[PDB]
Amino acid sequence: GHMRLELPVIPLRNTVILPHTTTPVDVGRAKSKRAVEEAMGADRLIFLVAQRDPEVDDPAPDDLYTWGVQAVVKQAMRLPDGTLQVMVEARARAQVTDYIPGPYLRARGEVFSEIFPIDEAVVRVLVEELKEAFEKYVANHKSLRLDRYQLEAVKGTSDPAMLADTIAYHATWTVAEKQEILELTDLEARLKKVLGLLSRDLERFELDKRVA
Image 1 (spheres, helix red, strand yellow):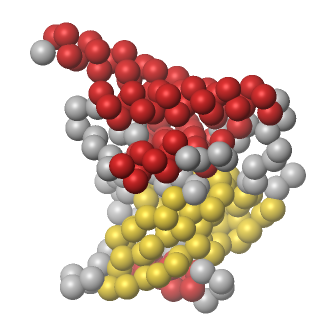
Image 2: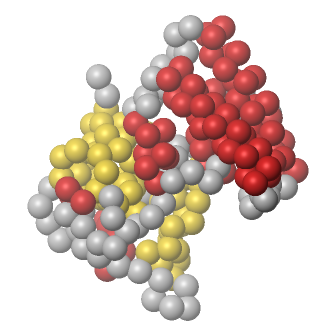
């Protein structure tokens, strides 16, 4: 089973947040600011969930993907425009299913841990494959540029779940693609999916290089 938490929800217009990342979320909507205030009132805990359609201004629960993350609001400060900049530390995958009627989005959702890697030796091999593929991916990417610290961090990650999520964070993949990664709670399947996307992209980059 999984812990079930009742938290406010921030709907993300066109981004997917992965666990093991700390990122700024700029929110302009009143209901989103309300959700942040409510999360501050109860240990900073919040759910973040991508919208299916970035154009929806006041999403119903149904307008949001099922999978998101449970996070901690580490900081929230106003920018010069009304904008609230929220620093979110994403901690865990969440299946955010059961919403509560009210003046902002609030839901009960199941939060997932990682469990011990099951086939440990297979997972260790996939970790090595992922690190090698990621180095090539960044080296051959025509738009994405990581500094030495970001690359070092991926190479130096020994936690397979953190590795896969960090790669997925950096990679230029669509909302749908990152949602597919979020929903893979099985570690081996998640590692293989991320490896698969990297490998496909490496082949695509070679094709784009030829045709240009």
